[PDB]
Structures are given as structure tokens and as C-alpha cells.
Image (cartoon, rainbow, N blue to C red; front, side, top):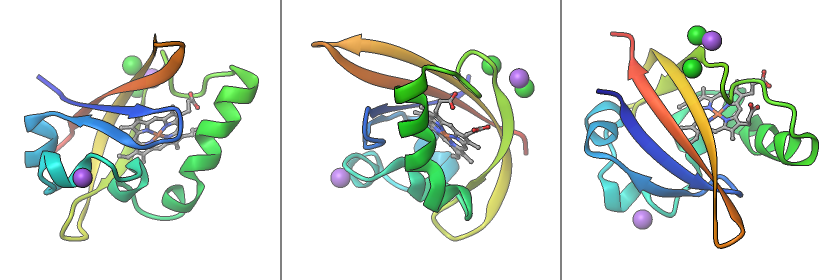
Length: 105
Ligand code: HEM
Ligand SMILES: [Cl-]
Ligand SMILES: [Cl-]
Ligand code: NA
Ligand code: NA
């Protein structure tokens, strides 16, 4: 029953499920088009794009297919513990990443 989020190869949100709206505080329309780093606190925020670049040029996963409990940040600035699972998919020869987010609250 997790929240689902999809981003492109550059970290830009492409889909934001209903549950993601309730969890993070942004509407689907607002989230789409924004970098996924708006959902996290520092230092991950400023480093997330590097996380993605690192994976695309090495193909060495740290969270994909592994999973981790991390800290997410709501629209009102408050942080919470969440479990994160990530998958990779191709469409039109382009990479997209699918994320499942479980609020551990
Ligand atoms: C909401 C808070 C999130 C946090 C705190 C977060 C945190 C992180 C961290 C810590 C890493 C690097 C881990 C390491 O190098 O050991 C990472 C990697 C990654 N993140 Fe995020 N992330 C979040 C959400 C997402 C979402 C929703 C997606 C996908 C839709 C996403 C996609 C990725 C990708 C593609 C990687 C690189 C693959 C890998 O390293 O295995 N992240 N993230
Ligand atoms: Cl997992
Ligand atoms: Cl885990
Ligand atoms: Na938007
Ligand atoms: Na894990």
C-alpha cells in the first residue's frame, strides 16, 4: 500500500501517486516537473543528483533492489522515517526509476 513515485534519468518527477500526495504534502501537479530532491533534507538533497549520476555511470546499486530506511521531508519542513525501494525500467530507450515509499510513522 506504499506511495509510488517515478522519475526520469535526471531525477525529475514524472508521476506522483495519490499516497505520495498525502505523505509529502505536494499535489501531483506541483510535484511533477520538480527534482525528486525536494522530498528530502540535507545533505542528501544537495547530493541526490550525484547519487543518480553515480549509479548510471557505474551500474553499481546501493538502494536499487536492496532497500533502505531513510528520512523524507514533507512540504511543511518536517522530517519522517520512511522505507525506500527502487526499481529501474526502460521506455523509448530512456531510463526511468520507480520508487516505493512506506512512511514508518
Ligand atoms: C524521499 C527521500 C529520499 C532519500 C532520503 C533518498 C536517499 C538516497 C540515498 C541515501 C542514495 C544513495 C545511497 C548510497 O549511495 O549509499 C540514493 C540513491 C538513489 N535514489 Fe534516492 N532518495 C529518496 C527518494 C528517492 C526516490 C523516490 C527515487 C526514485 C523514484 C530515488 C531514486 C534514487 C536512485 C535512482 C538512486 C541511485 C541508485 C542507487 O544508488 O542504488 N530516490 N537515494
Ligand atoms: Cl527493498
Ligand atoms: Cl531495508
Ligand atoms: Na508541475
Ligand atoms: Na534493505
